[PDB]
Length: 443
Ligand SMILES: O[C@@H]1[C@@H](O)[C@H](O)[C@]2(O)CC[C@H]1N2
Image 1 (cartoon, rainbow, N blue to C red):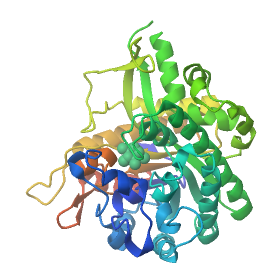
Image 2: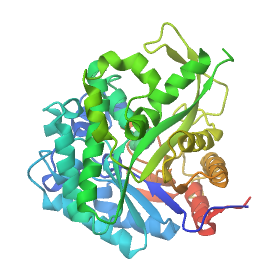
Image 3: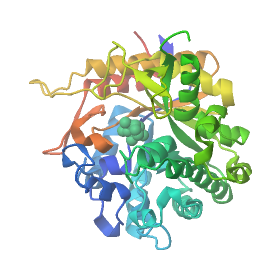
């Protein structure tokens, strides 16, 4: 058996635009994901977050599922444009009311809210003013964060500034695959920098406003392995420093970007970017690591960053993501070893498989059970070796809008039939519930 520490926080996670629907209900402003997904060609099948899981109406049912499963924490995000429809200035009480009801309900039921302040749905009004490219976003983000802290900080005690700021900057502004859909490397690195400045201003405001809570930040991470014994080792070093937590944690803890990020990208950063570093070093309470997959990596002279991925004959999810459970153990060990944060959480881990409802009314997702079990096991290991992991969040409670893939990728432990909005708890949800009840793995 593999038992976790007493009071370890087993959770599930979602994001506002991915589950809520009703993006313009009750005075909400447009988000960049609203305008991006309404632009032909940007999202698979023309899918949008207009309806999604209709969580905007079905929130109570969904929380009742969390409760019935005995899950002890819920990570969810707040839609900035529901709260401040123009990004700054006017506060929409109906946006506040929506999340107030969720928060109060979670607390009544003994579920710990973990709130992600920004999970990618930037107010469109602010994108018109350059969004993450504009230095002034540190101000706008601080003002938004302050509103949240003042309204909810009496009840919510666990906060996350940013979800996956690498993806926000690079996939949003370099690759152009996510909102706002830009392809400019100089804009992408200014977004990296402004994301850090905004994160730090929000933490600063948190300290003035919420005497008792904890605040952190969440990063995407891959387990990069070298294709050979060669510069392949260094291509891995670059991918780690660039794509993983060091891009952001080296500034936060050490006051500068990682060395190989600077070798690649110094020309793209603002000229006097070091001037902002002491403020960026604002103390954080925990690091959230998201983890899904491993990647074989090789030096490649012809690649845009001199690194290409090498396909491996390994089990993959419906995302095409190689299943490499030891990766979650590696990233946990590596974060302690490099930055030694006081607390760590796995804020997302999960898998997309092409789930079907069988004739028995059930979703027999043994592939997802196997995936989760293996990763929970590797996380257990890291704990046994002294990593201060305080919690683990399954992505996702529900099948949802998977960004540019639309509804075609199902990550839930709860199946959503989008034609009726019916929720069907998958085998993996029942399995996970038993994990949480037992506080760990047994066979
Ligand atoms: O695929 C996951 C997605 O569903 C979540 O919103 C995210 O936080 C961003 C990409 C990855 N993790």
